[PDB]
Image (cartoon, rainbow, N blue to C red; front, top):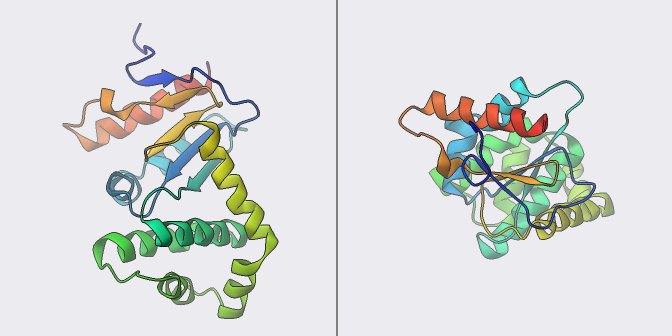
Length: 188
């Protein structure tokens, strides 16, 4: 076929029930993830091609960057809770990988302050049990699918995108193949 298990995607041996429709995992320490966000705009191109009524989820992971990695998973929970993902994603990536000015939880916090979230509001979220359960959700989703690498995208808790099996000669063409593949799996 044109789309084949083990080529543009893989199938999970152990499917995950009740999983989000489109589930993406990343880390701010993850170099391909940086590319996916700032150069390829994968999430946004997948959205543009998804059917109506299909929601997209994006979670941070703990397994890169040790202590700062966990802080970032909690910061991403704060970002989801306040709905400020589109204002902190780029400065977090750049702070971790480009300028390397993010070295502590305080530095992460600075990124939110500079993005216009008030200190009082950030600290309240950071320490909230709503953010706690949001951290729990990120961890459980990753645990469910045996996640050992990012970037990763899972569709309907059953299919895992396989970007290694796509052409990377042209960045635009790669992105569309990726997005079309998500759409195909979505309609499966």
